[PDB]
Length: 247
Length: 16
Ligand SMILES: *Cc1cc(C*)cc(C*)c1
Ligand SMILES: [N]
Image (cartoon, rainbow over all chains, first blue to last red; front, top):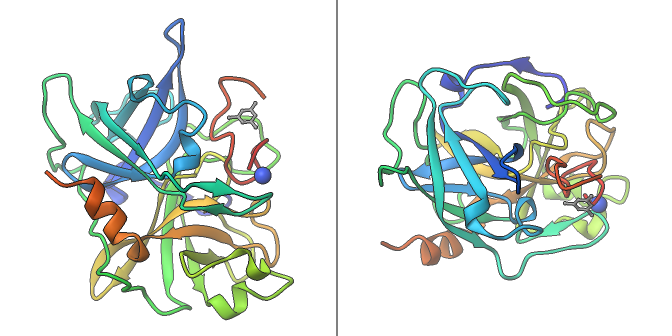
């Protein structure tokens, strides 16, 4: 996250920190995600497409730091890693950039809600906040596009939704953004998501509920003028999410 | 760029 504020997991308790184990046994961060039910984390397919084997991944819930353990965290293996079969990218745009991770602890349990772990509600079919709405994004992504290190403490910031009309202007992204995506950014272009924040939530209050409106997906640079974050539009993926999470 | 890259296809990443 560029700009914004350091936070703690209790302020974003649906935030999932996803890591991959390497031959040798070193573990590095991959991407963010969101807990949408006790056994289910949603994230972005681009985060996994290079290494699509579920056995490589670890998911932490209730974790506030990147490379350090925090009290109240819980660790899960990935029982099912579901990538969108129609994922594609161009130079910039990612389509169908949505992934599901079924989580299970070694003791065979799904998440249990606590002061540091809560699910986030999904929106109703095609239900989104009106543009101009202020939303939150959170992650362990770079704090400046030019940095090589990632913050060790979780960050969050506020960004406002941008209309399709404005986002589809040529000096923005033009026809790169579809109805299956949402744009969001700071009016002054000072705060944004960045590398490392992919797969994490764009959370909005909608019909008076904290809702997962978007998933951090793509954008040109980070915190550049007229170049908003682009987010997978969750309310337009309810059938995909439904048909892949049945019990 | 290497096997340890974080979010290598994310915004501003080598393959983003
Ligand atoms: C070095 C590297 C790593 C990934 C995941 C993707 C690309 C294009 C390059
Ligand atoms: N990219």
